Amino acid sequence: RWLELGLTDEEKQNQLEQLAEQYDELKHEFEKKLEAKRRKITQGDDLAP
Amino acid sequence: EYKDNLLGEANSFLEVLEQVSHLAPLDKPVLIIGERGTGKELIASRLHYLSSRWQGPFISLNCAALNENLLDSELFGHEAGAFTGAQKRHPGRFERADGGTLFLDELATAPMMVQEKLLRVIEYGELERVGGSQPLQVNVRLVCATNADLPAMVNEGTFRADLLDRLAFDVVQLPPLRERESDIMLMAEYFAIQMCREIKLPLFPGFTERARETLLNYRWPGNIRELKNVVERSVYRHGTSDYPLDDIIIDPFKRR
Amino acid sequence: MAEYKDNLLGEANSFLEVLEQVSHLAPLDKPVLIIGERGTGKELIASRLHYLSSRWQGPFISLNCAALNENLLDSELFGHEAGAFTGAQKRHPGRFERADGGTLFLDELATAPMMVQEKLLRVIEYGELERVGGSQPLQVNVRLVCATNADLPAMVNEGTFRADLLDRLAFDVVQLPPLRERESDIMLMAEYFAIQMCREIKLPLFPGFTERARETLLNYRWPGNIRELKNVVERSVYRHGTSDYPLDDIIIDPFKRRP
Amino acid sequence: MKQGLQLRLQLAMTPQLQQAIRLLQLSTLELQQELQQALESNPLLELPVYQGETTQTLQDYLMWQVELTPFTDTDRAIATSIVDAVDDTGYLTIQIEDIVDSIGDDEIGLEEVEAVLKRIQRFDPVGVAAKDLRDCLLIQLSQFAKETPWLEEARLIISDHLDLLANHDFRTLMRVTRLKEEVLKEAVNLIQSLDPRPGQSIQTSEPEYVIPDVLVRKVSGRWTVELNADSIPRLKINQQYAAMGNSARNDADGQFIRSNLQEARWLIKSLESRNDTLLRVSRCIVEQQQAFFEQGEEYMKPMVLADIAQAVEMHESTISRVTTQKYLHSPRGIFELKYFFSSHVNTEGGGEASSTAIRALVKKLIAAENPAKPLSDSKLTSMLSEQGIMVARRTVAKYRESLSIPPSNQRKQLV
Ligand SMILES: Nc1ncnc2c1ncn2[C@@H]1O[C@H](COP(=O)(O)OP(=O)(O)O)[C@@H](O)[C@H]1O
Ligand SMILES: Nc1ncnc2c1ncn2[C@@H]1O[C@H](COP(=O)(O)OP(=O)(O)O)[C@@H](O)[C@H]1O
Ligand SMILES: [Mg+2]
Ligand SMILES: [Mg+2]
Ligand SMILES: [Mg+2]
């Protein structure tokens, strides 16, 4: 968003920082669930000896 | 790189260093006419990190403290179970030599026999003290260093002609302690900073120019870390480098 | 029976004739004792004889006397077959025993054990040797090889060598043309060493040297006969380190204070 | 000072623990065999049919056809004798001459034997009783119609040109057989699908045979290794005889029974301690396996008897006897203890260790080189240079023979 162009630059700056934060937060959380699932994909089964 | 540490602003320190650099690819003996508490070891390092085989072994074993006549025979080798009470030669020095050079400190005391045994090494270098084992050579170079007076040894005959000669291929006079005076101010501050940092002393006291003058007055022939030693003394004299530096300690024997 | 001349260089003095007499000796296997400057033609002479030793002659058993510590120098001397001397195990055969037929590469080290001296006297006794606990004598064989660097007759008058040290020693003597004496292949072996030196330096071209250097070379004593000069030569090579760049001086006495 | 050896620092040995180590180095199958043959005298040392279905086994399947085939008594005897010495692959074990000798009839001749074999040569399947298989593939192709192309080229090659294909010498094969370029390979391929060891085809079924002795299940990293409980031997002290000894009027005889029982108790406890020492050693080995087996044999450090015995107080002979003929089933599966150790090397991986599955997968990649030809030892050396670990062509030939790979100029094949 123009990297907080400064429309209010005060809470809009603050809100924008918070929002980008949450955005990356979601990106990471999504990738994390993705990685756990993908691990489960090739997680592998226990056959008899 | 020896951290480039021990800076000698005496451009002769540099000149020595340049000789060293020329010597660096070079693989032949060298004497370093060192000084009492000077630090030929550190410079020999600075060389070794730059050695033509800088990747090569770099061991520091001097026979100055050769309290055992047999510590020698060891250093020359041992048969596996030679004499007995033992398994094999503890050959570490002989190890460093192959794929390495030779470095020693204060070669004065050597049993003359020990010395010329070293002679039978340098020209050819058999597997030695090996209790009859067949010979073997260590791809060994060399470097020499001392504060002794070589003419004094020559009068003493301390180095044999074969010895003094084939032993020696270069001569590295450490500048006298006071020789490298601008270097003294240099590496002096070098230590000053190094200390103020590593001590984590919250502030650096700096230096009193009067203390600097008094320090320069120290002939301080010993300065190897004897510089650093008197430095630690002075640091304690300050005790804490928070205040600006004036408390300089040289002679610590003094009570009160 | 081959050349193996190796870096036997600079014999333009009668050291050539010295070599000739050496050759005259070379067939005979009897005791060898020589004389001359340490680190200077000397052990090169040793190589010379080692060539004089038939290639098929055997192990050039090198004898370096400045070693041997004190005692079980005795072990490898007489031998050590028993227990409690050399890790026991097999009869440890001494370097003396190591040579069977080999070179008695006796080095004139002037160490204290005339004790040793008498031992070697028995080493040179009847062609025989007997170990530590060495339950039997064993009639041994080896080529015999000594040399010198100092006044053996004086030390005899000085009593310093066992009289028999020399008495058994030296079927004849073999000295060296001193650096103050030999003085002939000066430029010659000078250039030979220089060639080797530049080649190792991989110096692009032979610097050349001014005649002032050779004038000094005549002027120089060269107390160490062969190497001290040779070291000097390589030292000139280094202190210059330039290709085709004609020399005008040499490096020998770094003890000379710098200017 | 004056060094050497000097006096300082006996009794009677017995083979007790020595026989015990003889047992341990011996495999637990026969080790339990002795354990039974031991505990027998030590008195204090402790439907019928189901499915019941028969099968053919091929040779009797051949006999089934022979029964329906018209045959005489001598013909039946020769055919049955031919059937008797028959291999799994379906090739004839004995030559025609050995069969003639076995018939033991002067009327029986090599020609009659050959006629009987040929009438039975291709009944079921084609290429039965191959008799130094070569004409067997010939009869198999003859069974195929001539309408298949390149049958002539394949036939001429199989006639007397087996050697040219033996070395994969395609150039010499073309120079000899005058076989067509890029077309003789077609005859070669038609020959390649010729049901070799066709009798081996019938044989397909087996049961399971590997004994899990220890079990490491990779329990939450650093596997929880555990031995097999039932496989671990154990005796029961004769508590009846323990109570049948003291009260024995011969309190001497009964108390001596008690003493022998106590000694055997010592023996059994020592065996259990041997098991437990092997077990703690297995704990160290499993600590190793949590990386090695988990990284597989490719990333496995070569270990030595010295190395392991150092981690324990067990003697090097103690361990060296302890693991001999030992195998454990792991997450990977049943793996032999003798397999655990490996020789180290001068590779520039910064260290010394063993090739193993690295050598195996190296053979894999050398094969994975263009199927035109096998990769030479220089290919292995370059592969190791890529691996950054030093390997040599003599070393490469060594590791390849360890992986038992085909030779560089022997495995070249038409792509
Ligand atoms: N250039 C230098 N840089 C750092 N330390 C030095 C230097 N020269 C000497 N020293 C110090 O002197 C102490 C002893 O040094 P030195 O006298 O060189 O060893 P030696 O006693 O073998 O000559 C060493 O621990 C080293 O820290
Ligand atoms: N032709 C030569 N040119 C240059 N140097 C030589 C020559 N011959 C011998 N030297 C040098 O003389 C040194 C001592 O040799 P030598 O006197 O044989 O030793 P030793 O004391 O064992 O007899 C050697 O290190 C060698 O470098
Ligand atoms: Mg020192
Ligand atoms: Mg010598
Ligand atoms: Mg006598």
Image (tube, coloured by chain):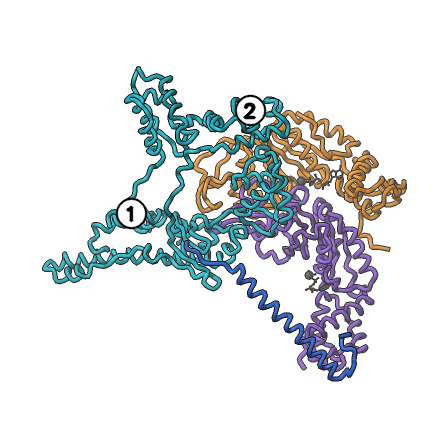
Chain colours: A blue, B purple, C orange, D cyan
For label 1, the residue is D51
- Dot 1 falls on a residue whose secondary structure is loop
Q: Residue placed at 67% from the left, 74% from the top? A: A23
- Secondary structure under badge 2? helix
From where the camera sits, is residue D324 visible?
A: yes
Q: D271 or B194: nearer the eye?
A: D271
Cα separation, mark 2 vs mark 1, equals: 50 Å
Q: Is residue C81 above or below residue B237?
A: above
From the viewer's perspective, tell me whether residue B25 is left or right of residue D231: right
In-image side of C118 versus C177 (left or right): left
Percent across and percent down for residue B233 are: 69, 75
Looking at the image, is mark 2 or mark 1 earlier in the sequence?
Answer: 1
Query: Is residue A1 shown left or right of residue A23?
Result: right
Residue C181: assigned label: none
Question: Residue, x 80% and y 57% (percent of image)?
Answer: B16
Q: Where in the figure is residue B190, as x and y percent of width and height? A: 76, 69
Say which residue label 2 marks. D152
The residue positioned 82% from the left and 57% from the top of the image is B15
Tag 2 and tag 1, C-beta contact below 8 Å? no
- Whether residue C167 is visible to the viewer of this picture, yes or no, is no
Extreme residue toward the top, this view: D106
**What's under tag 2, amino acid-wise?**
Glu
Categorize mark 1 by other alpha carbons within 10 Å: few (<14), some (14-19), many (20+).
Answer: few
Instruction: Report the chain holding disc 2.
Output: D
Residue type for callout 1: Gln
- Residue C213 placement, left or right of D197: right
Q: Within 8 Å: ligand 2 and the Cβ of disc 2?
A: no
Question: Ligand 1 quadrant?
Answer: bottom right
Q: Where on the picture, by quarter, is residue C249?
A: top right
Q: Tell me if residue B19 comes above or below residue C11 in the rendering.
A: below
